[PDB]
Image 1: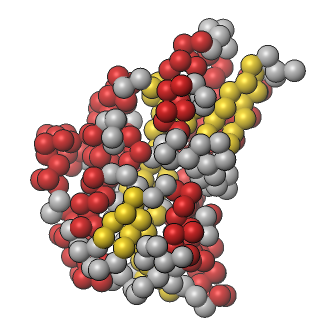
Image 2: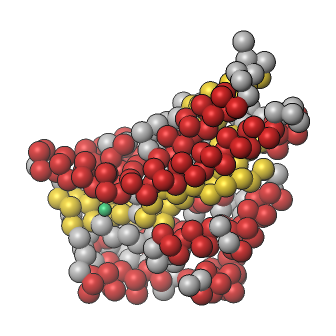
Image 3: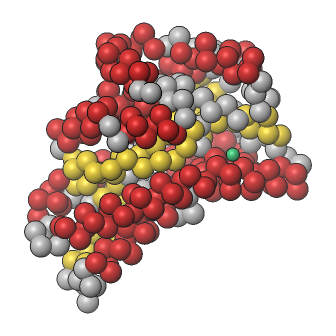
Length: 310
Ligand SMILES: [Cl-]
């Protein structure tokens, strides 16, 4: 019935803001094209995972993806800017950066490496968890193995507090925590609960120590070939979906914290720790110390532009 089909691939649960956003995109394309185009969304790495999605887009075997910033850092080193610990003060700060000058500079870089860069999507600020002991101060992280996404900034960040970071694809994280391959991880609350990382960690600290978000991209050769008269509807669909995703993400921390809290009370197998300002300061000092290592590959003046956004 559909004359054309589009394959979206991502690594998260459909129950997250990002997953709901992809499904909303898919639904709106269908409606706006009166059934001529059908978008099929493969979540949870069903079609391609962290390690395979990029090439897939290059070759046109997948059409649309929404990778986290860290996932771009081998193609575009500067995207590591958004991984720096404590770089974003809050969501107001974030969105002024993402929908402003710096956001555009990084889109443009991705565009040059052969992807069609569209909009930024939100996950949330990241939190430390462990199976070994409570993480209250930098001191506690020392000697522990942590999963990270593939980013030199994140491996520097954990090295700075004496931990052992290890890159693993998102789809392997639950099993790796369950089997002791790593002691802990850092996640936004959205991924922490929807992937059941809560069921395989004994301690969660609301550290808010770094940010995780996404850049929607499309396959350049898919887009080159896609029919000119149907492109406007795809683009409108995505615009609407971006607005919708960010609304779902605003709700998300409160909803997820309630669910994680109920799980901890009912199961007795998770303690949730909040930090004192004293504790927060110490995290900021230890983790920001890494910034100068990255003036060369990210750009000192780029980091300063972000810090200056009021
Ligand atoms: Cl909250």
